[PDB]
Length: 71
RNA sequence: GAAAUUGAAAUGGCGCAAUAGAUAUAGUACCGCAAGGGAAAGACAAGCAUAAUAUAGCAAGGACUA
Ligand SMILES: [Mg+2]
Ligand SMILES: [Mg+2]
Image 1 (cartoon, chains in turn cyan, yellow):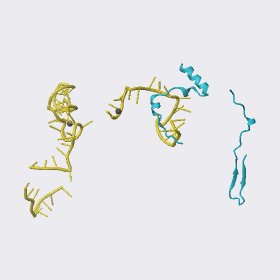
Image 2 (cartoon, protein in one colour):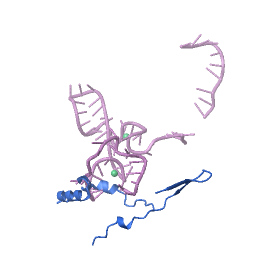
Image 3 (cartoon, chains in turn red, cyan):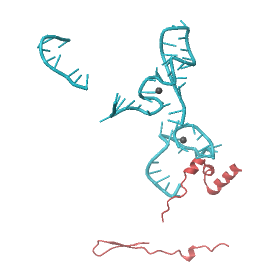
Image 4 (cartoon, protein in one colour):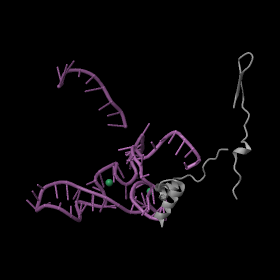
């Protein structure tokens, strides 16, 4: 849904792209132990087990607790 | 590798500071049958602990919110 148009001199391309709204008809009304724990978490979040095991103090201390923040 | 020949006057350290300077705290201890050999030392390194560990690998780098 974009309108392309060179200008008369042909030196600049003009693109008209209005934002199209979602039609009302295209919408639905609003409705009104360590082992087993890690298996449950992996099933819940569609991950593997390895993510949920802890890490040693060395890794934990290596993690930066005051990371730079942008925007 | 010569000699002939020639004819110099007169308390200190750009030395060390205990692995250095004597081997030297001592020619002792100790070693050797013996001759001999011959030391060491006195005034937050490594290793650990606080705090073991998490898939993958020269152990880092690029990074990354992490
Ligand atoms: Mg000495
Ligand atoms: Mg140390």
